[PDB]
Amino acid sequence: MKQQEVRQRAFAMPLTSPAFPPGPYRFVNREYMIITYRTDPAAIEAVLPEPLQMAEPVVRYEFIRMPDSTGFGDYSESGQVIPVTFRGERGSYTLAMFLDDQPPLAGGRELWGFPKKAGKPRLEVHQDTLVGSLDFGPVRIATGTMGYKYEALDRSALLASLAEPNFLLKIIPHVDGSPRICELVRYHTTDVAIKGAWSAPGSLELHPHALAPVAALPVLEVLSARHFVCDLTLDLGTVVFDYL
Amino acid sequence: MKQQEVRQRAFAMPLTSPAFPPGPYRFVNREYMIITYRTDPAAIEAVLPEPLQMAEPVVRYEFIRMPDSTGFGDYSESGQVIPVTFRGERGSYTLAMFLDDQPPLAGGRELWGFPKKAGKPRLEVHQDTLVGSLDFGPVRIATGTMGYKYEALDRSALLASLAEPNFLLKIIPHVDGSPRICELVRYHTTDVAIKGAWSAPGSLELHPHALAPVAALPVLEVLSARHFVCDLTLDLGTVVFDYL
Amino acid sequence: MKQQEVRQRAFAMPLTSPAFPPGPYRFVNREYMIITYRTDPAAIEAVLPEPLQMAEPVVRYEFIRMPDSTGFGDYSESGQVIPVTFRGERGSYTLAMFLDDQPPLAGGRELWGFPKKAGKPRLEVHQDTLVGSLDFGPVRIATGTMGYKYEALDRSALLASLAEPNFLLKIIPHVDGSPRICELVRYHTTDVAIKGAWSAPGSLELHPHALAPVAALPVLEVLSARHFVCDLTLDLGTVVFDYL
Amino acid sequence: MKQQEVRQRAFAMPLTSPAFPPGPYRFVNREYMIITYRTDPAAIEAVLPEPLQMAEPVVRYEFIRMPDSTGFGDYSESGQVIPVTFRGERGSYTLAMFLDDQPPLAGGRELWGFPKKAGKPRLEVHQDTLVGSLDFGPVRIATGTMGYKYEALDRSALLASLAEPNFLLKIIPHVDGSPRICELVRYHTTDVAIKGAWSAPGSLELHPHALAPVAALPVLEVLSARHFVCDLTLDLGTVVFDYLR
Amino acid sequence: MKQQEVRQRAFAMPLTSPAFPPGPYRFVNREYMIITYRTDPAAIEAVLPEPLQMAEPVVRYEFIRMPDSTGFGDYSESGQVIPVTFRGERGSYTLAMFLDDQPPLAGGRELWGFPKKAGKPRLEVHQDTLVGSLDFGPVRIATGTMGYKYEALDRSALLASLAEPNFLLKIIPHVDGSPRICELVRYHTTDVAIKGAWSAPGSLELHPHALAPVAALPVLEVLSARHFVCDLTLDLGTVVFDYL
Amino acid sequence: MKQQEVRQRAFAMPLTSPAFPPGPYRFVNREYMIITYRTDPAAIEAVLPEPLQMAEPVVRYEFIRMPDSTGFGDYSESGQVIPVTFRGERGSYTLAMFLDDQPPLAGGRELWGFPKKAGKPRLEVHQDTLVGSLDFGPVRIATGTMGYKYEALDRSALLASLAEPNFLLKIIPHVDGSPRICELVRYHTTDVAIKGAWSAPGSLELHPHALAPVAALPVLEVLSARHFVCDLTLDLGTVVFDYL
Amino acid sequence: MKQQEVRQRAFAMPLTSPAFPPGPYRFVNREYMIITYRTDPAAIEAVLPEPLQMAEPVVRYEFIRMPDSTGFGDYSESGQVIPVTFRGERGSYTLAMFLDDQPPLAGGRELWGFPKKAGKPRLEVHQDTLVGSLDFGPVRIATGTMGYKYEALDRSALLASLAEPNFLLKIIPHVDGSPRICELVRYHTTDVAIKGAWSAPGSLELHPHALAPVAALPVLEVLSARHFVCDLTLDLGTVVFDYL
Amino acid sequence: MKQQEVRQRAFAMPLTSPAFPPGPYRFVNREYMIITYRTDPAAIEAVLPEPLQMAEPVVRYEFIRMPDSTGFGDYSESGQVIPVTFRGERGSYTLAMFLDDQPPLAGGRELWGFPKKAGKPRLEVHQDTLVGSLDFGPVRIATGTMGYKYEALDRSALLASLAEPNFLLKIIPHVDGSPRICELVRYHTTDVAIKGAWSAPGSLELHPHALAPVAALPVLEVLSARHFVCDLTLDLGTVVFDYL
């Protein structure tokens, strides 16, 4: 298999059996618990890369079920998202995620630049409560709870939420340890169909961990909680600022 | 978190809590079981990317324990390695690995370009038999067996095998899915101390898997088995050929 | 809170974190097993409150799954309902009900006046059989079985039955133990969308219990068994008769 | 079953097999662990309904075993009680309670107006520590600890709290959702026999929950811990303010 | 229970509580994993009953979930199907099935003449991998694997495959052991709705069993893998050739 | 494999690997618990096909262990048998059976016409009591008990019992749902050797089930109980009345 | 414990509590499953020690239950036996055994010279299938399967096979590692009673193991399967050829 | 024993079988996790006994494995130590300690006067994370985490810290409950050989407990985390201050 055949088939490692596939990336029945909390503004500023700019000092803490995902399989995710502005546009910055499936973890990192690590997220209804949890090894680092579907939420506002740009700092080292890729990436979730969306009382507790430091954006006050189910496509991202 | 802080600080994602640290990457008490088997030369040719050239039509099947790994932790690995020459120099090519710990998986892939996937390798003595196994979710894909330290091995010769260059094909996608990095990488294991090294009868059985195709290189005849324990440093690789 | 705003805010206890929310109460994919059986006429007459009037001497024994219930969560229900007339108008009377979730138990009792107790109902397919059970603590008190979807059920008869009036006897003691509320309440399930509906052969065995006396309406003869899945709204009730 | 006989028979639903019976409600060998903690005064006034007034800014956090309870069975309970005055008379206000047995749950709510919800309270000695815990489904929302009977308490003093009035805001919705009952209820625990009472160092930790917000009253400092066993009759309450009259 | 009641009522044994009901036999959400493999043409010829003629020397190995099956219940199936022509028309031939539910096993055999035996098929997503397995008592006889929904399939073409005739050889013994029924049966799946259809890499391993000889058709090379979900009606078959 | 080869090898499906084999059918160490009870004569008449004629209004309820059975393996059985007369001959009619092994269940139905279904029978001594049970899925449908070997029974009378003809209504649908086989079948158990045979106090309890309606022949009074162990051969049956 | 007591008392170590007793070695109810398979004649030649000569290129693979064995206890065995001739006489050669009980392992090896190792053989009926398996620590190395007593076997012929000489190569090392005993040993099974003997379809799968190389004689085609139960006496062997 | 020899023999209770032996007390492969955190100065001042003097307001929280401890066995330890000065001399004060082995608990208390209580500390690598925990009965009261060996730690600073003086407050009541012993004790760890020593990012969460009040020194800010393995001798102490 010649030089140009290699260059032509190359998408992801291993060449002949890639750790992940090309898309499209389609998600069916994504289920979100999102708890939004006020935090120390100084705690966001210490972690937000310029030229991104801080908006509200809030954090979106999320627990996501992805039972049906092309190329990737059946998995769950938990993460911390921060509202930002970039060039007059509102959007989000993903600071941290954790997932229980390989292909979307390698794929997430190597293709888009999602800052993903391994963990055990769960999101399930126990009788009357929706309970989100994320373990990292034997250690519980996040527990969220919500009432069950108390109020229907505005679906227009939700679709506008899912339409905003999502920014990521993609960093990949060169063989020598210096960055070979260091860029702000913009991605969109498109073809959204909302199956249901609700609000209800919510709660969040975070625990410190040396290798999963979600707790360094302290929960000062829980502001809102939303729970929705939707289908969508994770579109390929585009570079919006190349630090290199 | 100023703009040029980012491009000088950036090593691995997440920028502020990297998924793996910089080395040196030191390994104490790695333990190897290596079953060398003869395969179909045509299966080797099918996967070998030029300018690499095949040598003997053999596969070195590895089960490796790494209980003490700087920056990475305590874990196990299994994989398929093939003798190769590049520009006439004899070395190795790593076709497939599987590991049970995320930092060395991401780090292996993003820094050197080891072709790593997730799986559950084990290497254990069960009374009279050293047993290596590799499971990928609920499916067994590799089982190797060895008698226990039947005869001491010529260490000076072994250390020779371990001085040879190891070659990797590093592939990282750009955000749009075309290759952003596509290169052959040369790396050495250095500062090696062999604590012991043995030979004994060996066996190997492989099973098909859509996502872990080790059985694509069929075990036609087992040729040798080696078992050894060592400390070593995984040095950073160099680019020896850039396809882009 | 100010004495005035307390009145304005009061819905259910606890005032500041009510044991159940207001609604509307929407149900998605309720799944029913109903076994209609002939019983002793005298047993029915002994429990039916005038001004309610007995229609035929049958009991509909229900096993219901409610996997998706707004404000309540995900739960199961079992109990006894009797065909009734009130002022000439054909309807049903709920004698006993059993649930494994507390918000719909309190809310059922305090809002509409469903005669609810705690219990563990289950409704599950085991290979070829739909099996309904009700345990009350360690004692099984109801076991129902049906074949799986032998014949389509008349959607029109079904929708007309669901459109009927349901009567409940709401009783709530005053702090002195005398009745503070004692009324016949009429309610409706509306916005009914049936997803599937079948008949099959069916069985029912009931067992004695001092605190869960379903067996007091003995199974003389099983008349029919229906299985259906639907979405509906549990509308608020209205008082049709005040004993006080 | 004539409509007249219906009215005569009516106490609690279901008419012919009430979810709970009538009393008298007797409790034998009721065991308490009470951790008193100072909280944020602003947290208390937000949840205290006028004409109640606030007394000292503390919360009495409770874990109670009721192994022998007439009409109810054998169960445990946990929750939050605060010091209050109504018309200048000093008493308690129950903010939240959680139990593992339905009859006292329904009865608690529908008769007296106790603010009750389901949960899994436990109270047990583990070697040297009395350990009280509350779980709400999979989530731990309260953990409390004490030494084991370090110092005896005077009982005669203790009975100073048990004879005080207890106040409850009783709320039962009408079929249409607006309040049918909305009154403050006064109840007393009478027939109190103390079998033993003790103090010891204590601890408390509380965790957030959307549906069980005990942690909304933050533990700033633990102030005292008490452990006691008693027999007790829970008397029927009386209305002392009717928001709806 | 008069004599001519018997001959007009008789459908299946036991006459008064038949082991399976009459249809229509409707299936909602059948899920298929099909691994198509090339085999020894001589192994196919050895089992193919004339007047059926072999076509390509391939086997379609199936693992199928049927969670909602009218009259039959919720169950799983695995089996070996071969492309065939009869009187020049292209169709299929079912060589072997295995199921975990009795009504469809007896019903399959006695009505259509599906060559059904007992076993324990499973089809499940394990993170990144769709895994089909078939156990016959304690022995694994089939393991298949697929990546997860790598690429959407041409549905109109699929629906084409599913319009083809399916052929069965129905054999029932007379009480004396000579064949009482011995016929080729043609049946169609009709009213088909494809909910989704995908392709992805595939693997298949078979193991010998004296009583479940799937391995008699050896996996020489895996050619394709398909995964799809559908609703369909299993129509009654017709006799196309009677050997007697 | 030609047309006539097919017709010549055809015994049971699948042609090339029959679900059951030819006999002879030999049973070693068959162990029976038989509880005979008086029932409603109207309950037998509703289930007994003419030209069979009712004898006593009793039912033989049975629990059988078949640990050693040619062609079939190791299994257990439970069933309801009714005494009948046909053409001046005393015999039995089998109304219902349940077994935990496939080959004898398919074989029983397709060859002789035993009205067999699937279930979990057990027959074991627990200390002082012989206990027979039959579950159908998670549901207990029959429990019998006997004292242990209180009295030896008449072996001449027992052999005469095992010598009487056993009648079965064999029904097999045609592909179109109409009966293709509908006949009264007579079979004998021959070559009987009785190893031991006893009577003792006995008891029976039956539970309703929609798909296993053994309970529709109510236990009004337990009359007798016998327990024996024997070897025998289940001879092929012969047609004694063809409804068709 | 005088010097010449030792040389007249000495049978097995420990002298005062020998690891196995002298016989006769009587076996009641040995049960055999034997899968006869054709293999590579070249694999047979590679292991057959002259003056033994190979006969058919077949292996008799055995799984044997010995529940009642004088001096040895209750245990199981599995092994590989090959047809042979010595000085023109047809007999057997035992290549490999594995047992789960020490006295017969030591005794087998030190007295006759059976080539015994440890392992975990099992032979059990699972419903319709006789299943033999052999595990060596955690690795399965042999799985055999048979239908259950399909047809009675010609016993007089069987007893003929069991009258043939069995040959063993006995090897014991001297303290210095050179052979102290190295001889061909002939032994018979005598006083044989066949309790039953059957044939049925068979299967065999072998797996590699460094220390249990049964798979070195590959299953090319399974030829027959036999299942039988017997009592027999293992007589002491004789030396028929002494290499020393 | 004679009254004189009692005095001569007395070391620890029981006289004739002392709860712990004399020593020297040698430790091999102690493994420490130390997390240094800033706390509230007032909390430290509230527990520190004059003549001891407060140095910086930090607490070193320790999780220690002692797998090989002469006279004591194999055990783990957790607790709190504070940087201190005494007469100008820099050292440490041990506030609280927790162990799962009784000989070092009694011996620690009675000989040096370590302030020991019972508890269950653990220190373990879970894949990529070093996890320290302390349970006290059913309550977790300390959880520490570190990355694995990110950077070498300064051996010189380490050895100097281990060479420092440790102070303890030895208190032992007289039978009347008044202090019989009340003294500041100084001790040293000598013959220290460090085997490895590292730093990495670290975390600590503490929890309230009435009998194990570690939380009384609140974690305001984690300053550092060190991991090391060493051999050392726990030398006898000396009194430096007698309160009595």
Image (tube, coloured by chain):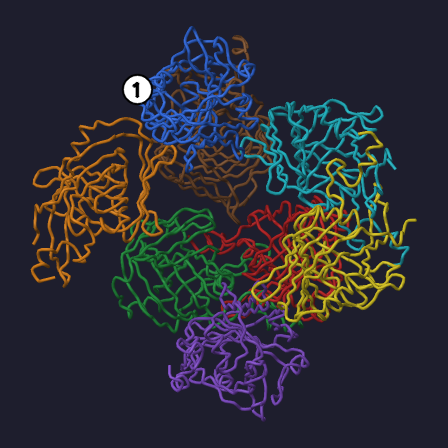
Chain colours: A red, B green, C cyan, D yellow, E brown, F blue, G orange, H purple
Nearer-the-camera pick, G221 or G135: G135
Residue farthest to the bottom, as pictured: H87
Residue D232 placed where, x, y %? 73, 56
The residue tagged 1 is F191
Residue H75 placed where, x, y %? 46, 71
- Dot 1 crowding, Cα within 10 Å, few <14, some 14–19, many 20+: few
Q: Is residue G238 left or right of residue D87?
A: left
Relative to B86, residue C95 above or below: above
Check the residue under mark 1 and report the chain it is in.
F
Residue F183 placed where, x, y %? 45, 12
Residue farthest to the top, as pictured: F87
Nearer-the-camera pick, F54 or H173: H173
- Indicate the quadrant containing the C terminus of chain E: top left, top right, bottom left or bottom right: top left
Which element carries disc 1, helix, strand or loop? strand
**Looking at the image, which residue is at 53% across and 69% down?**
H119
Q: Quadrant of residue F73?
A: top left
Relative to C54, residue G134 above or below: below
Q: Is residue A133 left or right of residue G32?
A: right
Q: Is residue G193 left or right of residue D189?
A: left
Residue farthest to the front, as pictured: H2
Residue E46 visible in the displayed image: no
Amino acid at pointer 1: Asp
Q: Is residue A154 left or right of residue A122?
A: right
